[PDB]
Image (cartoon, rainbow, N blue to C red; front, side):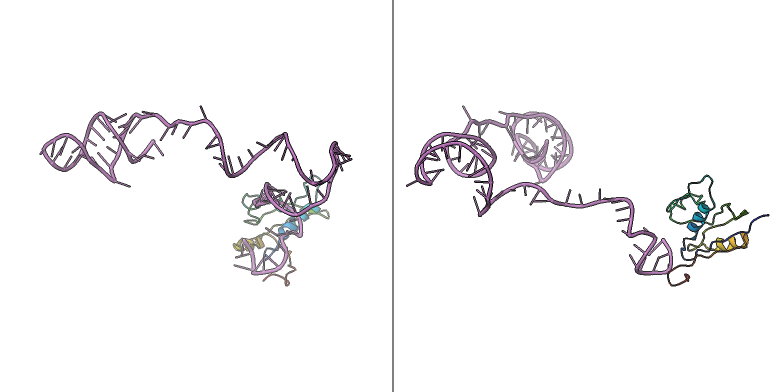
Length: 107
RNA sequence: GGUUUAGAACGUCGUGAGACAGUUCGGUCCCUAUCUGCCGUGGGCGCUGGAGAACUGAGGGGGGCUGCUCCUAGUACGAGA
């Protein structure tokens, strides 16, 4: 009926939220811009976030694929005030870490 | 415009005339370029018989500044920024 929640643990500036945006593009449209390099929509919401080059807080965005709901949130992996991302864990059961190509997963 | 002419005034100094890089207001800045120099532009002659072209190029001059944006690449670097 509903759809399982999905996380986005982009540790060490993984950029996983951009992957959430591209996933938002793949789940489209039928009427969407398809996003763009940098910010860029991708549910950036508040000003000073996309302008800052990184989200100041975790967002949310409705999505659908394979005939089912697919909520997802990103990124909160920056810094630094990551406790809100820990709050995000209560907000969803799923997860999807974005592993770096640099010496494996970021510390 | 300032400083330095003659007028006037204030502060100060002096018995006073006056004085004060103390201040204030007002106040005629000439020259037709011979030579050198430089910018141009010619005439005379030479270059060896005269003439018309066309280059060669010794040499000399001019020009030479840099922003930003994007890409490379958000890559190297960095725990992140």
